Length: 188
Image (cartoon, rainbow, N blue to C red):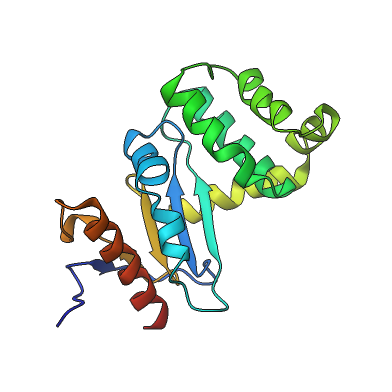
């Protein structure tokens, strides 16, 4: 058939109960993740085809970058708590990978301050239990899909996108087939 288990996607041996409908994992240290988000815009192209009543969810991971990696997961929790993901995603990717001006928790915080988040507001969120729970949520979600690498995307806690089984040559054909596949899995 056109879509095939083991081709455009794989099926988790152990489905995850109560997972987000569409769940992406990434790291701001991850070069392929920079490509995915900043060049290919996979997230945005995926959301362009999502059925009505399905949310896209994006979690950060710890395992790249040591202490900064965990600081970035905590900052991403702050972004989620404050609802400012679309103001900090580009400057965090660029600060970590392009300019390499992000080397500490303070440098991460500067991105938020520069984006208009008040200092008191960032600090209160950073040290909040709501944010500790959001960090734990991201970590648990990774364990539950038995995550091995990023970027990665899971649908209904059941299916894992398999970009290795799509075309490489036209970025746009690849991006379209990825987006088409998520929508298919959404309805499956």
